[PDB]
Length: 147
Image 1 (cartoon, rainbow, N blue to C red):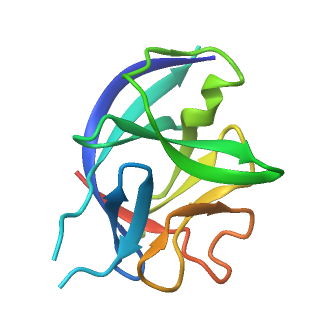
Image 2 (image 1 turned 60 degrees about the vertical axis):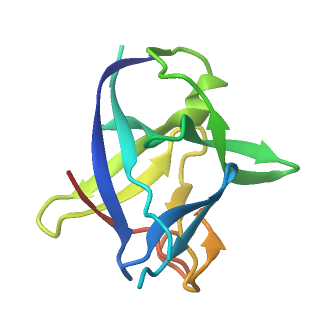
């Protein structure tokens, strides 16, 4: 279903200017800086065999994925090597559609495994990054990326 093309590194902030920080090897949180380091994203751009992407945490050998946990969709970080082919339902956990609103320069990320579910941060600082089916509704699911 998807075939790797290339990766590009981006800075990322949510629209309330929180950045991502890798709090622990399995925990990404969003906070306001100034202290510690912001995460950059290594965005792997794919082609169906829409902007399907994988979101790598630059320098830490981790990729974001969406999986069922219990009975709830859950965003988590997994150790994964760069993936050339995403050719199963299972592997689709790593794919997100990058949805750019070009004129405003903002971006949302929608899970391919869990359509309708969007990468989101809390309105409060120092919470985990998660996913929601109510994007931008008592959460922030809109970001600004810069190369």
